[PDB]
Image 1 (tube, rainbow, N blue to C red):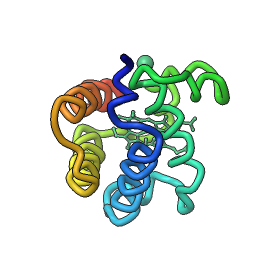
Image 2: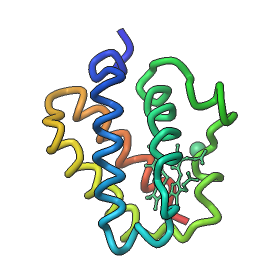
Image 3: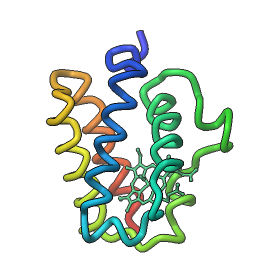
Image 4: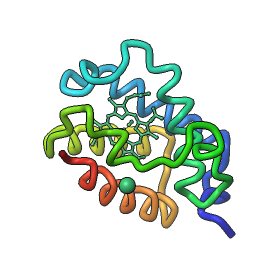
Length: 118
Ligand code: HEM
Ligand SMILES: [C-]#N
Ligand SMILES: [Cl-]
């Protein structure tokens, strides 16, 4: 079954809200994000749902995701990709994400965040 089913709607929503609480405290990232992260988190949940083989919530609403393009306006450094990743690792610790679903998600996120570097 789809890897999204190994995490689910509730835990995914908690992973992502936790993540954006950390982003909002992270001095390198907070400046380049919106001041209000309410909408970003809503869109990452849709996106992460799609990314984990669940319904394509993101495309359905915003269109074709082409993330590297959507990210190009912003100054994504290697060191910023690393802060995002660090925030995300911490967020996973907090919700107690573990095992093969943590390995699959995070391993993919690592490859994606580096592909965001511009
Ligand atoms: C390299 C570190 C990253 C930085 C600094 C970064 C930064 C940003 C910023 C500033 C926004 C604008 C917020 C908004 O428009 O709502 C954004 C949106 C978004 N990011 Fe990233 N991002 C990074 C990596 C990633 C990764 C790895 C993913 C994949 C899970 C991702 C997925 C998204 C999505 C789905 C949006 C919303 C796009 C939209 O507005 O439709 N980003 N990001
Ligand atoms: C991008 N969060
Ligand atoms: Cl892409």
